[PDB]
Image (cartoon, rainbow, N blue to C red):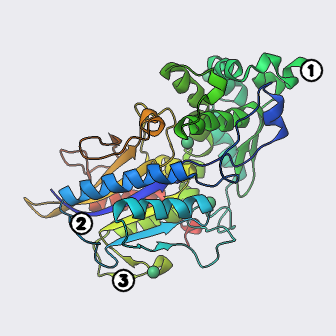
Amino acid sequence: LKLESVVIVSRHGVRAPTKATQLMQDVTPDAWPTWPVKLGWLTPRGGELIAYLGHYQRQRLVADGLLAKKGCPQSGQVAIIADTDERTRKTGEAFAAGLAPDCAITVHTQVDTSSPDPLFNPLKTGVCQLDNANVTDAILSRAGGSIADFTGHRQTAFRELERVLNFPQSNLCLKRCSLTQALPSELKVSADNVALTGAVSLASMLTEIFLLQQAQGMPEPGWGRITDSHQWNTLLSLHNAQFYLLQRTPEVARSRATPLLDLIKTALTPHPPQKQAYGVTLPTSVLFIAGHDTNLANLGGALELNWTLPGQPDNTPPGGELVFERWRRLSDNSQWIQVSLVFQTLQQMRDKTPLSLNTPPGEVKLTLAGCEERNAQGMCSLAGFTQIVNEARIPACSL
Ligand code: NI
Ligand code: NI
Ligand code: NI
Ligand code: NI
């Protein structure tokens, strides 16, 4: 099998919290540790971790014969697209720096940096709209039938989070007991967005913040109250759970992932090279796309890619990569698509461990669950991939 093309959909790297709310203060007696950069921005450490994945990918791709061992990749051979957020732009820069240091690979973004890019979510620019009644029913059904059913099955994790927070001594509690009841969680479904209020979204946010502390190398994440891998896995199930509901549900995911699906399909299809989105010439050898956890999850649910990540409690971790490869099978020159999730384990983030062929990131081989035409290695034919993308995408959400 000869590797011919690769498209990497990456979450941005380690970032500071996006917000600092009063509710965050009220649910713990302890002080949240401060971060070295503005709200939502990538930390220098964040950048360093992504650059390790770049270095790893270069080694790996050199071994696969796709990129040369010495020198800068030839022009256009590597392309990088990034959302307009500081944190995604800087993730792009960091990945280029690890992959091809001193080659100054351009990090492309949309023309306008101060407005949202619909490639990363077409709902947010009103390219298309969710069907309210359908999405409501679909998400409630995925929750176990109600949001009360959903929190009912996760009581243990909520109580783990309360322990870490010391929620019983918190201001909310002293006035008045439990997160899921003190903060009732409701599904809010609008034309451009689905959201959960209350305990479910607070829990998803706070547990991700603990993970980021750990990954940032902070001395005592969770005020020192998170002391083993079972606790990490337990805490982060609340994050994963909200994403299961709000981002993986196909009635949301398909719409929200549609421009990325078109871009990925374009990048992976043999075709004469041609300047398109962002003035990037496609197809080419490597395309790196720097976005958001939501994007990873939206693709996963649109494409019926399922995973959990061993040693990495967040299913959609900082720098986690959804890797699409086109491989040519030499026996009959047929074309095949492989999909994988490449990620640093939490310990690899915590120890800032340099990545390499002998010390690789974790990796989970995925299967496209709708694919009818599969090879021995679990890859989906190009034609099978193509049909899956065509059925999954929502035309009204295309750019
Ligand atoms: Ni964004
Ligand atoms: Ni149930
Ligand atoms: Ni350019
Ligand atoms: Ni995540």
Where is 19 relative to 30, above or below? below
- Mark 1 is on which residue type? Lys
Q: Which residue is drawn at 48% across and 64% down?
A: 93
Disc on the earlier residue, 2 or 1: 2
Q: Is residue 399 visible?
A: yes
The residue nearer to you, when weighing 15 against 240, is 15
> Foreground: 321 or 154?
321
Label 2 with label 1: CB-CB less than 8 Å: no
Q: What's the distance in space between the residues labelled 3 and 2, CA to CA?
A: 20 Å
Q: Which of marks 3 and 1 is in front?
A: 1
- Specify whether 249 is left or right of 277: right
CA neighbours of label 1 inside 10 A, class few (<14), some (14 to 19), many (20+): few
Q: Name the residue under label 3.
A: 274
Q: Name the residue carrying label 2.
A: 67
Q: Tell me which numbered mark, 3 or 1, is placed earlier along the sequence.
A: 1
Q: Quadrant of ligand 1?
A: bottom right
**Is 362 displayed left or right of 234 in the figure?**
left
Q: Name the residue under label 1.
A: 175
User: Which quadrant does the N terminus fall into?
Assistant: bottom left
Quadrant where the C terminus lies? bottom right
Q: Distance between the residues labelled 3 and 1?
A: 63 Å
Could you tell me which residue is drawn at 54 percent across and 55 percent down?
A: 254
Residue drawn at x 66%, y 29% is: 145
Amino acid beneath label 3: Gln
Instruction: Please say whether residue 13 is visible from this viewpoint.
Output: no
The type of residue carrying mark 2 is Leu
Q: Picture coordinates of residue 326 (x, y %)? A: 27, 60
Above or below, 239 relative to 9? above
